[PDB]
Image: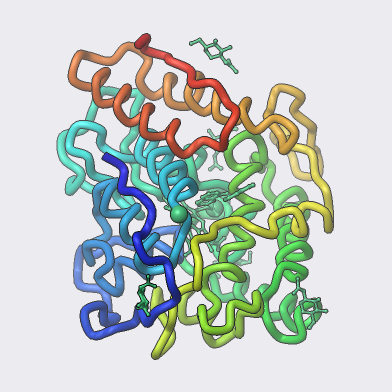
Length: 324
Ligand code: HEM
Ligand SMILES: *[C@@H]1O[C@H](CO)[C@@H](O)[C@H](O)[C@H]1NC(C)=O
Ligand SMILES: *[C@@H]1O[C@H](CO)[C@@H](O)[C@H](O)[C@H]1NC(C)=O
Ligand SMILES: *[C@@H]1O[C@H](CO)[C@@H](O)[C@H](O)[C@H]1NC(C)=O
Ligand SMILES: *[C@@H]1O[C@H](CO)[C@@H](O)[C@H](O)[C@H]1NC(C)=O
Ligand SMILES: *[C@@H]1O[C@H](CO)[C@@H](O)[C@H](O)[C@H]1NC(C)=O
Ligand SMILES: Oc1cccc2ccccc12
Ligand SMILES: Oc1cccc2ccccc12
Ligand SMILES: [Cl-]
Ligand SMILES: [Mg+2]
């Protein structure tokens, strides 16, 4: 079962004796998420970067005070499209035999590195998949984050910086990635993610939304908590996302095989239709990976889809692609 919320959600030291940072060993997997990467590199998750959904939910709550609903939604969304539903294992990065025997095509079980399932374009510190690497820390992109922090955040990363950088990244992908896609699930996650450094990488004794660049580099590049890092003082995920959207409101769309051809997609969900984002994720994205599953897969899909629905913001109706 998905873990419940923390019994005690106070700020506390999370870079502690039981959770030291260690460098990668051969075979250890890190991916496009600096949060999960850091949890793995401090042993909140298995240090090889392969974990169960329950391990992931417990780690994001314990290590960073990610809220339960967001933890559940993200984890089961990722697991459904990138994880092995039979073995209950998900790679936080590149596809690995460690997640076990694969299901039939067209399912990929590609880990979080898979492009276009969860991971997508206009990431802050990772390049678009089209440019060759959607997962490793990129120094040039991080230096741009520092520059935007200097220009809009007084040297710190905050929601104002997020609003400007989010837009810059979109516009750079429009200008250079002929395959740029910015619809549906990615349209939502691209905004929320930009709040996470301000909400979750800021020491919880401050919780002031102003992330310094030394801490930012430590998390984004080295998957390492600052010495003496306290987690956030209460559960939170994407609060302040409205600031980021309001800075430069966008419509969902994509380039259409050429640069500078961004074309709005009226079939995509947007922030006015959050339930549509959920329904399309299940009916189209998940169903297309598993169009006619065999018995054990069908049962695992339905279980994980029920868990996903627990993380859906209130008011949406559950959909059942494989029946009830
Ligand atoms: C709850 C389970 C989570 C999963 C499965 C997950 C997975 C992912 C994935 C696949 C991405 C790539 C999005 C992209 O293409 O840019 C991403 C982005 C990101 N995640 Fe998470 N994430 C989770 C929770 C968290 C938490 C708790 C934090 C912070 C503590 C966090 C911080 C970030 C950041 C900062 C980015 C954007 C990095 C960048 O653009 O350079 N995530 N996440
Ligand atoms: C919760 O944890 C905090 C910090 O570890 C501690 O001070 C407090 O006594 C615990 N109990 C409650 C209910 O806050
Ligand atoms: C290009 O976008 C398509 C969907 O429009 C996606 O299937 C594919 O993985 C993307 N390729 C790259 C390398 O960006
Ligand atoms: C990092 O991002 C920059 C700017 O988009 C790009 O030129 C470069 O190919 C990427 N990779 C490396 C290793 O810098
Ligand atoms: C970010 O920092 C800048 C400069 O200190 C400040 O003007 C702005 O109000 C801050 N934004 C947020 C959302 O804290
Ligand atoms: C998803 O499929 C369900 C039937 O299982 C249907 O009721 C619903 O309208 C569909 N949603 C979308 C957005 O296709
Ligand atoms: O927008 C989001 C909401 C909740 C969780 C997320 C995890 C990763 C990336 C984006 C997320
Ligand atoms: O309201 C939201 C919009 C987009 C992404 C989010 C991620 C987490 C939590 C809330 C989010
Ligand atoms: Cl919570
Ligand atoms: Mg990306």
